[PDB]
């Protein structure tokens, strides 16, 4: 269940863009406990990075990853 599940949020967004070749996947932050809308990219070396879904590169990267 989710009632007592911990919730993961984003507070800081990466300043710099990440090339598609370095991205393995993403997930969205849905929880209304979180301060703002966010995307977490997991890179090809499993590092997790907060990114702002308002930014266009973030949107396009998400679409690309969705396809493969
Ligand atoms: K300069
Ligand atoms: K220039
Ligand atoms: K191209
Ligand atoms: K212009
Ligand atoms: K494209
Ligand atoms: Na140059
Ligand atoms: Sr640039």
Image (cartoon, rainbow, N blue to C red):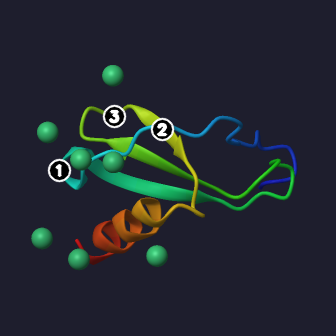
Depicted 39 relative to depicted 47: above or below: below
What is the spatial separation of the Cα atoms under label 2 and label 1, in whole angstroms? 15 Å
Left or right of 23: which side holds 4? right
Mark carried by residue 21: 1
**Residue 44, image quadrant:** top left
Mark carried by residue 49: 2
What is the spatial separation of the Cα atoms under label 3 and label 2, in whole angstroms? 9 Å
Quadrant in which the N terminus appears = bottom right
What residue do we see at 35% from left, 54% from top?
A: 25
Residue 48: percent from left, percent from top: 45, 36
What residue do we see at 40% from left, 66% from top?
A: 62
What is the spatial separation of the Cα atoms under label 3 and label 1, in whole angstroms? 13 Å
Residue 61: percent from left, percent from top: 35, 63
Residue 2: percent from left, percent from top: 79, 54
Of mark 2 and mark 1, the one earlier in the sequence is 1
Write down the residue under mark 3: 46
């Amino acid at each position: 269940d989710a009632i007592n599940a911990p919730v993961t949020c984003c507070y800081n967004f990466t300043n710099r863009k990440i090339s598609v070749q370095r991205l393995a996947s993403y997930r969205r932050i849905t929880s209304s406990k979180c301060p703002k809308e966010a995307v977490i990219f997991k890179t090809i070396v499993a590092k997790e990075i907060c990114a702002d879904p308002k930014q266009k590169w973030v949107q396009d990267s998400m679409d690309h990853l969705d396809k493969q």
